[PDB]
Amino acid sequence: GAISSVLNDILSRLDPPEAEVQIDRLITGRLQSLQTYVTQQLIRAAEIR
Amino acid sequence: VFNATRFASVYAWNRKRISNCVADYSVLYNSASFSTFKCYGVSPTKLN
Image 1: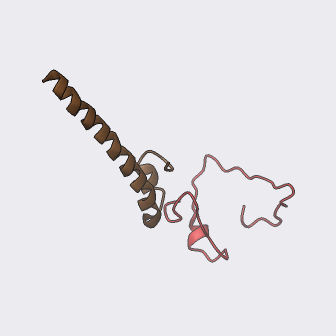
Image 2 (image 1 turned 60 degrees about the horizontal axis):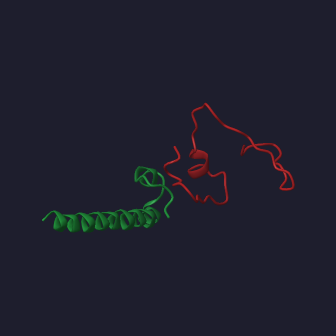
Image 3 (image 1 turned 45 degrees about the vertical axis):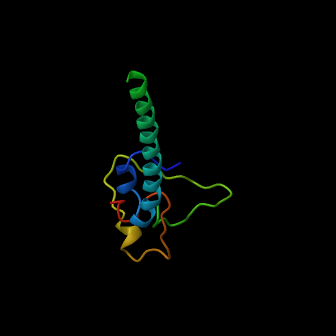
């Protein structure tokens, strides 16, 4: 939902008080991507165990 | 673009293309040649 997926496309593009909004979206999305990865691998470690 | 002798109309507006050149956006920020200056998708200080 942000303007661009790259940080430098926002850090070197938008002002600080506006860049904080878009960067907060990518950090929100990329963090849930890890929780889905770690959760899956943490289940596969049980099937292999 | 900005120091034009005559501007276009909104019923049918012209479009001046600018490409392959060294730009200097100091006219939009520092020089007193405008009443207001607001950017939407970019910072006004990083244009240069």
